[PDB]
Amino acid sequence: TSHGLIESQLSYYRARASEYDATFVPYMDSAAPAALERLRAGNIRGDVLELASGTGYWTRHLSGLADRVTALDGSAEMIAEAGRHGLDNVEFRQQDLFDWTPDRQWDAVFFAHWLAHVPDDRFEAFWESVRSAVAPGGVVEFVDVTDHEVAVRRTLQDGRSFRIVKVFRSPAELTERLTALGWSCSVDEVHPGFLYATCRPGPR
Ligand SMILES: Nc1ncnc2c1ncn2[C@@H]1O[C@H](CSCC[C@H](N)C(=O)O)[C@@H](O)[C@H]1O
């Protein structure tokens, strides 16, 4: 995967930030209760890190569960949108997640719809950075879509064209891959098409 692809994908979300919620909210509505049940199940506690926080759809929920949230997104436009929620215990930071190495640790790491934007060749390095971010006894949870070209082309009507990574991975694929990377995982289809995963890092 090229930097061109990574930048294109990020640029798409920079362009979409102001209209993101109008699309995302009704998209997520049916699966939201099942996802929120797992989110509130007791692992999102203490100091929480969110990756690819977007408009703060999940950040709003994390803020209510955590003592403090650090929320990272590559788009300043997204961070600006996320500020609308007025969450007092959240620090937003602009960060390209493909350049990211943490300099502290958190009790829980959460991301929604992020992993499917991570191509196979960047998967291991991403999980190495996540591993470093997890405090002793910490946990990683995530939401994504299952599957039952690495990227899709999306062209806006003005002509802007983007490539966006779309690698939906099954519960079996995710469990197998994360096992291979030294994690223990439970990945469950909480609503048709939608997965919730809980992951614990092994000794290495
Ligand atoms: N290279 C990159 N580094 C950090 N964030 C990136 C990125 N490429 C895309 N993103 C962010 O990934 C998010 C994808 S959409 C998912 C947003 C949110 N988690 C939700 O579920 O609603 C966008 O907010 C986009 O800005």
Image (cartoon, rainbow, N blue to C red):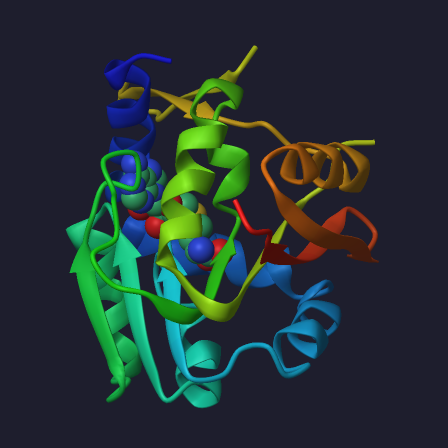
Q: Is residue 176 visible?
A: yes
Name the spot of residue 170 as percent of width and height, x first. 76, 36
Q: Is residue 155 left or right of residue 196?
A: left
Res 129 → quadrant:
top left
Residue name at image x 30 percent, y 25 percent = 6
54 to 6, vertically: above or below: below
Q: Is residue 182 left or right of residue 121?
A: right
Near-viewer residue (158 or 108): 108
Q: Quadrant of the N terminus?
A: top left
Residue name at image x 75 percent, y 70 percent = 34
Near-viewer residue (174 or 72): 174
**Residue farthest along the front direction in this orientation:** 203
164 to 2, vertically: above or below: below
Q: Is residue 3 left or right of residue 76?
A: right
Name the spot of residue 146 as percent of width and height, x first. 73, 40
94 to 38, vertically: above or below: above
Name the spot of residue 47 as percent of width and height, x first. 37, 79
Residue name at image x 54 percent, y 63 percent = 25
Res 31 → quadrant:
bottom right
